[PDB]
Length: 111
Length: 50
Length: 49
Length: 50
Image (cartoon, rainbow over all chains, first blue to last red; front, top):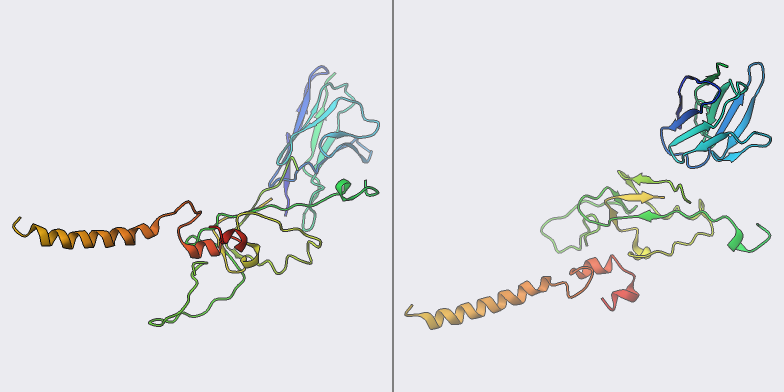
């Protein structure tokens, strides 16, 4: 019933820039939202839950913004250590849903 | 804080807004419908118009 | 509450006799219409938040 | 214009009756000018004052 898409497919920007990711919904999901990061050969880890609250032990560089339909994940500064795939989870209604998580967005940092 | 009273408890509130006009009706009450009769003194009800 | 949803209700029959079990301990205090005779009414547009 | 008086009588009566019947659609400060509409729109306690 709920379907999402994650854009961009991939990003690339030097060490001093800011990388941003859009997670948009077919219909509004309110604040209910979560952002996940997996290193290669590593299970994903929660970074932003409720679309605003920082997780535990995560540095204060990842910003979640937006509410309802459009959500943005913005990183103030990269250090070539956040080069991984990020996903957004609906965590709102999963009665008949093909995938709670969205598309994959791999971050590439050229240092 | 569930220990405190209902004033510190979650309340789910659903708000409904109508327009309440009897002509372009698309959301009506659950009452049934009956065949009309002509040329007789009757008390009718057309889309809420009694 | 800040990001309240909005729903459109149309092209359907609306019944209130079912609105007891789904939301127990409900309070339907409201304005602009008598709730006692909501059964015999028709609505052009209904929005649920 | 010879028969002005009788025509005046007839016109006076007709226009007075027409004004009386037309004034029935006056709101008089209600939400609606149809008492049926008032009955299906409000709880009695305010229906009495309307």
